[PDB]
Image 1 (spheres, rainbow over the protein chains, first blue to last red):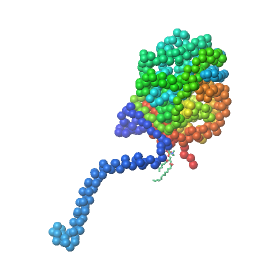
Image 2 (cartoon, chains in turn yellow, green):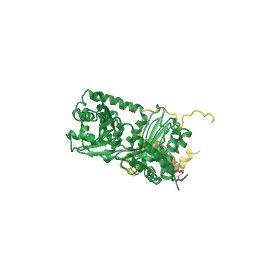
Image 3 (cartoon, each protein chain N blue to C red):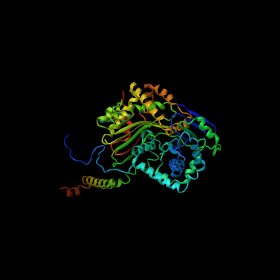
Image 4 (tube, chains in turn purple, orange):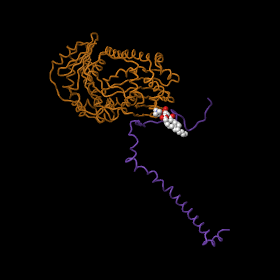
Length: 93
Length: 431
């Protein structure tokens, strides 16, 4: 076939990774494993952990934006009520 | 073709054969690596090595005797070969080493010199004997946390932490009378040997029994010893086979003969009546492979081992091999079965009747220890010829079809796919 350009991924047998030596892996057939019911008592308190580290990165920017949104909205409501028609003429045009 | 065996105080088993030139005598104990622990693993192999130590070996060489020992999983054996005339002097050396010198062989200068040798021995094995290394790990994962998982040569860590006391503790718990059988092969008569044995009395630790344990069990799993620096990939894959003294002991061995063994470099091997060869030779999926039906006391392994330099097509090797095995349950032919019968007899014959008595002793000893007797070669052939296609199918449908497997490999095994992919090939889709 036609010459192919070099990439950063090969295929089974020549993936392109470094030569591995010394690493030994072990696994057990899913058939021989305890049927899905053990993901509790042992895997419940452990869970929810991967959002206890992340929630701040989400919550703080969320909070900043929710507050900013609430503020601008409540201000608009005031401007269009009787009490704020004076301020409305001021900030409008 | 005579299987004679009688019991007095000790159980004596012999198989006399007129023309032989030499005679082999030895004791075979009903305990091996399967009786050890993860921590004293390698004690039996260590025993074998001192029994063959320069000191004990020189004493037998002066007398004109040759020593031989073999450590297996279910048993252990110590054999002394001699001329047909010195059949009595072998027994003198046997008793002198198991009662008199069972304290002289364990000297602090002999033990350390031997330990240093089995360490370089077991290390060399792990460093270079990849096919056997892989086969050993196959037993390790297949029978994990069970007796059959322990390797016969023992592990480097359990070996270097072993002491003289461990040898003694094992010897005093397994080298018992009720866990032993004296075997004699060569040309000597049964009555000729039993007399020399019943002559010298003394029981020595009689009535004592070895410790018990837990039953062996197969666990579908795998161990991957990846090593990209090796020039090939060596793999072994198997299902739970048949234990010795199983109704399907022969059906299993026949099934393995159907696929047999192969060697891509031997012209004649490429011509065998094996359907799998049509698939693997096109792109040369491997340098060699060999099927086996390993049988032990509590269990066994049925599968194959293979070696290959075609590292980007290992998945095709495994796929074609497993598709062929699928056939045993659904479409194996009469002629494939018949070809297997003929070849099984030829190989079973070449094993049971070789021109070497030491092999005969191990075969006889191992059998009598488990079933209390030995099935004659002629009796086997009767069982082999009686196997039908229906038998093989019933066996395969129970042992191979949609059953868990055990895998082990080393070398360039990046191309060996995940467990589930291999496991899925243990069957076929159907309406």
